[PDB]
Length: 234
Length: 247
Ligand SMILES: Nc1ncnc2c1ncn2[C@@H]1O[C@H](COP(=O)(O)OP(=O)(O)O)[C@@H](O)[C@H]1O
Ligand SMILES: Nc1ncnc2c1ncn2[C@@H]1O[C@H](COP(=O)(O)OP(=O)(O)O)[C@@H](O)[C@H]1O
Ligand SMILES: CCCC/C(C)=C/COP(=O)(O)OP(=O)(O)O
Ligand SMILES: CCCC/C(C)=C/COP(=O)(O)O
Image 1 (tube, chains in turn green, yellow):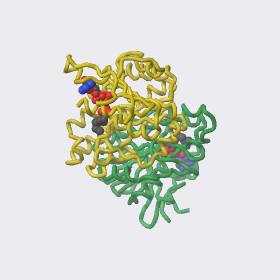
Image 2 (image 1 turned 30 degrees about the vertical axis):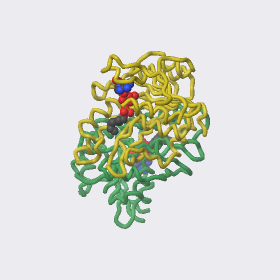
Image 3 (image 1 turned 135 degrees about the vertical axis):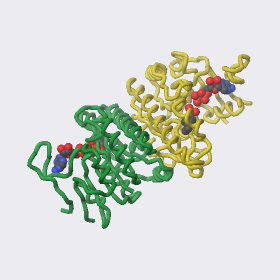
Image 4 (image 1 turned 180 degrees about the vertical axis):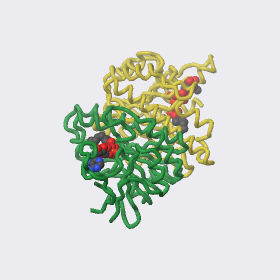
């Protein structure tokens, strides 16, 4: 099994609120289907969550009552975005269903707690891929807290033990600095010296590939070599 | 428990969707129903059905029969996507009326067993309601502990939330003035049952009293009639079917 995260940087326009990149997700879902590999797809929120959370300081928790309608607005936006991603997967013959973390799990000390793993495992047993995503989750100490797609990878990595982990973003890989502001940073090949090291072991290798490059995710899922950042270690 | 003055409402699929055409959302009804809910000012928790967003495909692929062949797996995932997309449109109407709510799909967090919806983890639903974000459940394809997948109903989703929060009132919004002795669209001779107390109209009368006691009552009001849902929530008496007494 290969755990993939369709990051918000490719599936959405992180600078334009509520903007869905339909042609990108449609191509990425087609590349996943053409690879023929058993996968579990996660995706981020992008502008379907980050734009409103920053305006209302959702990352700070339940500060005042003015954040309650904004938190529900983000929750509705993330669930709406997941429907569009699932629609692209269903059109490519990939049964999947949206699993909102804010509707089934809780958060505490910055971690997503999965007290009941049965329905998620039963969904994967039916061939209907459970699709978690970045969302606002009820917090046990801060009222509510935001979970990212990265932690959803960490939770699903320890639960299903995938053979490979893939992070899909709008960058060819990890650089020494921001490649959009610093145009001198080099592409870092290996990683042994982010959180890609917490989901790798003896054989599991984490990858960071550019979803904006066509057929790059397809070749990476097929075992061929592509431009990316590979992580290894314990 | 906590919701001492809560009113439990079902926006049935016959009034929020057009069950004659697949994947059709009644925009003006849900917008009017949500506005009627807001104008009442009562603390409420909304559940809705699937209607044409689930019944059309479930009948064609026999989802009620369970996982018999692999051909129903893409059909089940399509129903789950349709019910989630419909729940977004309902929540989108509640957010416009100033009522913070979030979709809580049962098929993505719960399991079923021989027709019974199992809710082992009550923390997320209880935490959302306490925060002010109304958890919204609905009919959906739910993984079954024996039959692969099963179909949960909006009526069944209310039975879980009624025993979870112990609400003060229960309202069932449908496309009918109330419970009749027969089908009102077929039997032009059937009469309306005003009060349901002591005795498939037998199973329908028995289902309403299961969510009633000495104080809490169950109502079956018409959602296609404007201002009818708003009048009941404030305490006015309208054309409906009330269940009182409990069991
Ligand atoms: N050292 C770095 N290497 C690569 N990208 C970086 C680096 N530092 C900052 N970035 C920025 O982070 C962005 C990718 O992260 P992000 O878009 O948040 O991931 P996600 O796909 O989860 O949205 C890139 O657009 C890039 O501009
Ligand atoms: N005894 C009865 N009394 C009232 N309506 C009935 C009866 N038997 C069948 N019906 C039919 O059931 C329909 C509503 O049921 P349904 O749409 O399943 O409820 P909901 O959509 O709220 O789940 C009505 O259109 C009505 O014609
Ligand atoms: C305080 C954040 C609130 C917004 C939110 C739910 C974000 C999801 O996290 P995430 O998956 O990393 O988004 P993205 O990096 O893929 O765009
Ligand atoms: C899961 C299969 C689809 C049928 C369904 C959702 C029935 C329950 O909806 P409803 O009767 O409107 O409450």
